Length: 67
Length: 67
Picture 1 (cartoon, chains in turn brown, yellow):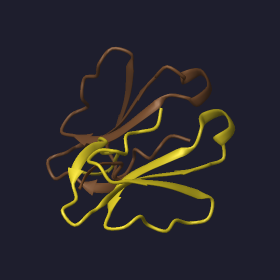
Picture 2 (picture 1 turned 135 degrees about the vertical axis):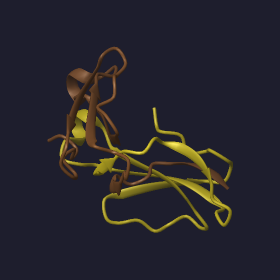
Picture 3 (picture 1 turned 30 degrees about the vertical axis):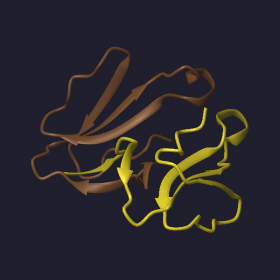
Picture 4 (picture 1 turned 90 degrees about the vertical axis):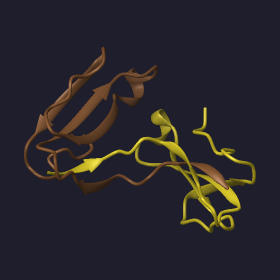
């Protein structure tokens, strides 16, 4: 069977990477639910789409899900 | 560098699977944000932890993120 999967958030080695990042943006219900979150890794801090904020950092696992 | 990753929700072939599932449960702010969602695949509809509801279905991609 083929299904949609929501894989668990986990920590991964990005051998070519030098920063971790946290992208945040507002969806339809941002007022009550808060900003959406995307966590990743990259060689350099990536440029983002319109309406997206990004925070980059340079220690392992420096991008936990925001509290 | 090692970082936390939120992988994109996508559709995947589970060759040994016969159902797709949608697990839902309430976190701290379930009143305003709605239930949390976990999407996956399994051979049979899995038994779930306390406070978790599960919906299983048997067509490909029958488990989209709830609207």
